[PDB]
Amino acid sequence: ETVVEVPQVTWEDIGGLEDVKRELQELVQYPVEHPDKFLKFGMTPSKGVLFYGPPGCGKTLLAKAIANECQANFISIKGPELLTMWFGSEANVREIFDKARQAAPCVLFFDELDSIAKARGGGAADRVINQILTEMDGMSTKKNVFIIGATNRPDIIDPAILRPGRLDQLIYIPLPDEKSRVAILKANLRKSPVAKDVDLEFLAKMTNGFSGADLTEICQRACKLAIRESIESEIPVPEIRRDHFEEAMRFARRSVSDNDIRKYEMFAQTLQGFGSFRFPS
Amino acid sequence: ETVVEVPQVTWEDIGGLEDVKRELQELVQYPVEHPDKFLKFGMTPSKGVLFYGPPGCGKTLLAKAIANECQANFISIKGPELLTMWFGSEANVREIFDKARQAAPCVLFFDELDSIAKARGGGAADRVINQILTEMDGMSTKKNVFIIGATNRPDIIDPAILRPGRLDQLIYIPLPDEKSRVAILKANLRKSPVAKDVDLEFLAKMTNGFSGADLTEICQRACKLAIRESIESEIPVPEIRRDHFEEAMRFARRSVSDNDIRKYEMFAQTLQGFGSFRFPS
Amino acid sequence: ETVVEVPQVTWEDIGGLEDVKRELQELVQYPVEHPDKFLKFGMTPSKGVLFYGPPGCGKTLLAKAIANECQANFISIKGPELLTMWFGSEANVREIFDKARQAAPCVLFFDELDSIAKARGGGAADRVINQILTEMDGMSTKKNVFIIGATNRPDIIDPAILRPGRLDQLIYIPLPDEKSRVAILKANLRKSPVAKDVDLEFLAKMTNGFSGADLTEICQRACKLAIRESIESEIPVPEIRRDHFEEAMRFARRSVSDNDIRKYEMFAQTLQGFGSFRFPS
Amino acid sequence: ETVVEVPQVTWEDIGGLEDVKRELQELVQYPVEHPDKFLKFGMTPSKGVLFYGPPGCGKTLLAKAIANECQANFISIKGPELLTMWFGSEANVREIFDKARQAAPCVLFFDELDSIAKARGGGAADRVINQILTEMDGMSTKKNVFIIGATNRPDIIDPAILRPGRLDQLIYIPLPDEKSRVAILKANLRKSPVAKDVDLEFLAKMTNGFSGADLTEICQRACKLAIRESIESEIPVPEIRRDHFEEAMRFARRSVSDNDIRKYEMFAQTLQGFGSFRFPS
Amino acid sequence: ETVVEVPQVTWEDIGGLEDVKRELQELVQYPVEHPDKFLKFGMTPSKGVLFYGPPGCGKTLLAKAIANECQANFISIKGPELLTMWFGSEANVREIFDKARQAAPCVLFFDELDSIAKARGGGAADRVINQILTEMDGMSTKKNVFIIGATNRPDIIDPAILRPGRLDQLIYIPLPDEKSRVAILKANLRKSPVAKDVDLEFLAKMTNGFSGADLTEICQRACKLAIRESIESEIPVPEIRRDHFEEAMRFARRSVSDNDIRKYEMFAQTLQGFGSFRFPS
Amino acid sequence: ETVVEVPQVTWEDIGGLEDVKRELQELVQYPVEHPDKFLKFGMTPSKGVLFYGPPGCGKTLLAKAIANECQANFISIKGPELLTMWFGSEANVREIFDKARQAAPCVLFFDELDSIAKARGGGAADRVINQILTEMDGMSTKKNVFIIGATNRPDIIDPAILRPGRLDQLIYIPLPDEKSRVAILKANLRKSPVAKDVDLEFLAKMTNGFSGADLTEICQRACKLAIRESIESEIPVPEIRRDHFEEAMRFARRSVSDNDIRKYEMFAQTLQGFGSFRFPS
Ligand SMILES: CCSc1ccccc1NC(=O)C[C@@H](C)N1Cc2ccccc2C1=O
Ligand SMILES: CCSc1ccccc1NC(=O)C[C@@H](C)N1Cc2ccccc2C1=O
Ligand SMILES: CCSc1ccccc1NC(=O)C[C@@H](C)N1Cc2ccccc2C1=O
Ligand SMILES: CCSc1ccccc1NC(=O)C[C@@H](C)N1Cc2ccccc2C1=O
Ligand SMILES: CCSc1ccccc1NC(=O)C[C@@H](C)N1Cc2ccccc2C1=O
Ligand SMILES: CCSc1ccccc1NC(=O)C[C@@H](C)N1Cc2ccccc2C1=O
């Protein structure tokens, strides 16, 4: 069944994205720690955020990290489960939201919620989507239940979701930058024994269009090469030599083509005038 | 379940639209206050109205305001509910109308009733819509039950709905004008503490193509900026200063493009000759 | 449930269409008053007529009037009812026809029976329509039950209906003429108090392309203006003054465009040679 | 060859359109009579106007009338001439513009200048159009040459012509109103002998959707009926009796369907906000 | 024939766009004033620039202004000229380029060179365009001939043009900013007599989505209203009163819809990574 | 007219592509220096090669380099020139080939000969292309004239060209490699004064998907920044500092998207089994 537990991954697992870090902090951590400030100005906190961007950029990791910062429970619903509600039996959504309700500080996370529209392609609408919207509107908003939905194809999302009182804050998660890349390497690589002069900074520099998944795959390949060498030795070397990394590098491949990056950037810009508005004074 | 209660929002929450305000007054308040006038001339009052216009213009607020002026109960059915009856279970419409019937002075309000046609795109027809029409025709019309339906896409509405004995009076709700804009700011902003020389009139003047939702977003952004500043101070300032508003303005965005406004104006004109007809005398 | 009662509307409600009035008289009133004459010549009376023409011309009123002249019970089935049995549950047709059969002098009236085809747009065929055809063929024709079907779009009617033993006599009901217009005004206006120099004949002259619905709307607008004036006076004038009319007239709008009228005329002409046939003598 | 002469038709020929009459007066008559006022404010007069509207509404009559009011020479280029220098030999446009240049107070009039695009249906552009544009831009504008272009289908006009320094003022000429209708009857009927109680005001009232061409056809038919009766008498009655008009009316037909009128109205509305702009004071 | 003169319009006429002003200064001024620095570093100056953006933003004005800064001759070729030598006679391109060659400091300006592609809708290619490319490649580049091409539809431009040795620097000219708007008003209005409390800054604030053409139309309308008032008075007031403006404003319309602005912004972004590249040090 | 001169560019201007360098050496050098070996085996040398690959990779530079190593004359025909023969005048091809024939050791180079097919989008055939084929087949092949054709879109080339006795050897020129990149920088940068610790090796490392044109743009931008700084100083620094480069780099963009690279690789693989064929021995 659903796992409702405080994630252990922290912000340091992705060193970059300080802007969205702060934006998330002020969207979940501020309503919860300082409700007395929110009822001062009569502001109603938002209860929905939509992550969009190219695959393998850390959207799930971002949701887990924000849940960890506020020590809020994390409930994760996957795309296959959404498609099984759709193909089936869509009343399970209500009990999912009830499970979230039981734990007041909950970051409900719908992963690839555009899967229904991907599988359906008649307008953008599915019984599961409408029941999710009904449950979301029904949420009192007094609870600390905060919904996050990650998507790779925001262009096909049903516009009904993008409404006030629902997922309204669209956040763009771009490909990792050099500092974020080295942080993503350090995480997911520190577990393995690495020594010699493996300059993770050099790899961060060289890998430019790579995503988190690509760096994960490259570290995976280096570990596998080390394991193969050690096995051949048995049939020592308790660390991953540089040679392993520089051999695994030439099989490194980028998952997202620059055309997709251009499309995501066009979307982000479309969601972007006055510029310098000043009162008469 | 359905909430059947007299709305508290008033006309002052939307300052403008005096023409449609009077038109609504003579469509709901006149049949109820002065039935003795209606049976004098043998006129049968209309029991249906269709609000159409760009999103976020106050159609729901208008329905609630007219219900408040007559002190009639308000029942609100949302688009997700309509779509779940469609995808489901359309016989719930009958009990919804029964609930409305129990309270004689009732403004039944169907929000985004074009949702079924949006999700369906066969011809313009739906089991839920036809059952709604059956219930509409069956209504005695002696009761004070008055139906209002709000739509953003009247072009795709099934023509079955638009007919005498059904939603016949089509009313256009355009974007707020400057006086309406300042009224919408004063409401939805007066709750929060605002001080200094924030000239809401100046904001009303500057925001020209904005809708009610855009002004709501801008006020919420200003409140959030004030909250962030106060929190940073703690980790005083009991009012939203001008700086907050003039910093939130540069993120202000218009939701309805002028192409959609042109389309709505074209529709309204199409629903618009004799000009000067006089008896022979 | 179904209302089975002799209509009270008479022929004078629509003063024109004397030709189709006589044609209906010889199609319903002749078989019933003088069955002995019909069995003399072995002629089998027709048991079906199809009304077609632009909307709001008085087809339902015509059916009620012919039922009233023969004092035959009137059973009216609406388009929403047909569409719900289609979307549902088509066996209700059998019990509807049974109800008609219980009252021997019955004018069964299917209104907008093209509604199913409109909602369906696969060839011209529907479960409810075929069951109606089965029940219509099964009718003994010894009973005085006589079917009438009103349509706005005869071009999409399933040809299965148009055939001997079914709806075969297609009758064209055009827009009202000036005499018919003044009659349609006097009826539905005489109930209200009208005085001064309201020249209903002048209004009939002016309104040329108008239908019954348009004139009804004009009269209702005049009544509403009078009611508004009287209410404002209270917050006298016990009659609708000529000013009220000549004011409401400038909002008068035609419902049927000239293109639709041209299309209906084309259909009627297509349903229309020998010209002068004579025996050799 | 081209006829360059001051037209004899006047404003009284078409009684209505006082608004566009004044507008044309201030576009042609003011730059010519009072250049000393134009050089005061540095205002550069416009040298182009595009008439658009349903056919047979008096656009050519309006051009001739404005030429007559200013006593400016009138040069008329027809649609067939444009299509022949298109299909042919487009350099003759320069000759035409030179002829206009010779007469300084000239109202150059291009009739149905959309004929090229109608015959062409590749983007909206033809060599003759571009040469007309070249000659129009080359015009000094110090001369008094003022271009007018009448169109029935402004939607297909090449956008290049709708530019500043070219045909920029688009004027909408709707169907005649009652006063305009009676004027259009009096003119083009006064020549013939009409007597008895022919009440042209009654005809103006009756004919509502009619254009100038339709009224001209009515008068033509009445004259033809009178001629036929007189000839039959010979093989007296030197006046057109009311019987002739009342018999010719029943053959009266409208040339422009209300769909086209609605399309023209939608275009005009598209070419129609601030509403109440005021200085801070 | 072609007019080859140093333009008189200056930068002050278009107040804003200081960034592109500097960019143009370093594309035309630096090569001409300081060739001794260009041959020092072996850098070959670019001989082509493409202006793109929404219509009526001052692209022609920008070309004239840059020509005026360097006191270089200005040759302007119009779109109709290009389309006529396309429909014709493309060898005249060589004559034009020879005319430019005669004057060494020349800013050759091709206006709406996308006109041929617009009129053509085969692939993107035209004999005139290819001959222009041939003559452009043939240019020695030792001369001071600098080509500028303005376009409203860069998306349909033949890619042949966009290449090193041709129009390579694509420059985006957006809608005027408030400072640019007030500058555009001050120019084009200062010639006329304006007095009272006409606050051009207030108009600049109010007009937000307006272009240069829209402001020019506003000023022209105000001048025309003043002229009409003065002429009526004659049939004094030698200044345009604030009433004239605040009356002309309500007729003000925006020429470029925000959808087109969004498209241009998306193009500019597409033409817009490393971010922080630094040497190892 | 055509320039027939031995190119001065050498192989060192692109340090990579040693494989294709040797392939070209054995296709032009060997037939020319050692005909006595070709007539020994009866081998008939090929007189045609087709360069294909992404734009801006040095195909023209490769043709010039091979012409330089053999000290053969170089004749370059451009795409615009082909398109003007096409749109015009294809008999000029014969005199071009005659000019080539006059110089026996000639490398005739047709640049972007796919330009005609691009402008044409009817099968792949063009009067100019067929005349080129005729002139190419007719050539004795005893002469030393050798034809090279560069194309960016080999997929749309007319297959008639890809025949024995014509352009037959298709050679793929991919994006520059690391050593090729550093060589392309060293050339095209050595002319300018560069000093400090500008580590061209580091730039070669970092720029991975870049083409020759992209590196040229980087170098030009750095030179332009240096020139601007020197001018501002004057209104010293006789070298391009590291700041100039590392600042120009962030504006660097990749001209060829990885999708195009994938398509070119797919084509190359398609033109790419036995694997290990050995005689029975
Ligand atoms: C927002 C990009 S969504 C996307 C991302 C990766 C892979 C594929 C896609 N979608 C598509 O390719 C569909 C095509 C028709 N586009 C293109 C596009 C560009 C910019 C904005 C919106 C659209 C859109 O709907
Ligand atoms: C009444 C505008 S309804 C609308 C509003 C916002 C966003 C989209 C829409 N519909 C459409 O765009 C469909 C297209 C085909 N149009 C255009 C149009 C203009 C004027 C009248 C009716 C139509 C219509 O059916
Ligand atoms: C009999 C007219 S039925 C009609 C009436 C009002 C509104 C719409 C319609 N149908 C249509 O418009 C469909 C189109 C394709 N037509 C045109 C037509 C003209 C004359 C005869 C038959 C047809 C027919 O099938
Ligand atoms: C401006 C109406 S032009 C017109 C007038 C009479 C007869 C025919 C036409 N054109 C058309 O019918 C073409 C169709 C596709 N429409 C319809 C329309 C309505 C409103 C605005 C622009 C358009 C347009 O381009
Ligand atoms: C660069 C916008 S060009 C433009 C400007 C104003 C008016 C019209 C147009 N072109 C179009 O609308 C054609 C359509 C198919 N689009 C859309 C678009 C958006 C962004 C980038 C390229 C394209 C393109 O080719
Ligand atoms: C050889 C790639 S040619 C190319 C290069 C850059 C930019 C565009 C193009 N052509 C195309 O895109 C046309 C499309 C339909 N493809 C795709 C493709 C892939 C692999 C082999 C042949 C084809 C082909 O004909």
Image (cartoon, coloured by chain):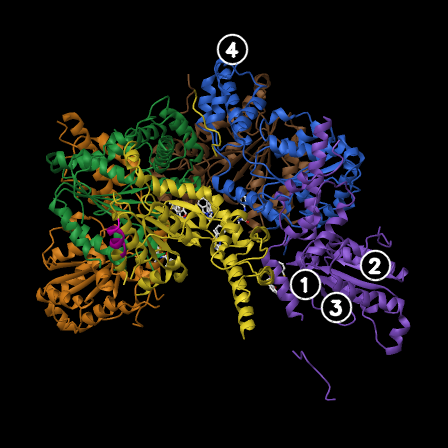
Chain colours: A brown, B blue, C purple, D yellow, E green, F orange
The CA span between labels 3 and 1 is 13 Å
Q: Which chain contains the residue that carries disc 2?
A: C
Q: Between disc 3 and disc 2, whose residue precedes?
A: 2
- Do marks 2 and 1 share a subunit? yes
Indicate the position of residue E83 as horizontal and vertical percent values: 28, 54
The CA span between labels 2 and 1 is 23 Å
Q: Which residue is mark 3?
A: C169
The CA span between labels 4 and 2 is 82 Å
CB atoms of marks 4 and 1 within 8 Å = no
Vertical side of E197 occupied by B132: above or below: below
**In this rendering, would B70 be left or right of B276?**
right
Q: Which chain contains the residue that carries disc 3?
A: C
Indicate the position of residue B199 as horizontal and vertical percent values: 48, 19
Which circle marks residue C67 in the picture? 2
Q: Amino acid at mark 4?
A: Pro
Quarter of the C terminus of chain C within the rendering: bottom right
In this rendering, which labeled residue sits more in front, label 4 or label 3?
Answer: 3
The CA span between labels 3 and 2 is 17 Å
The front one of A101 and C129 is: C129
Indicate the position of residue A105 as horizontal and vertical percent values: 61, 26
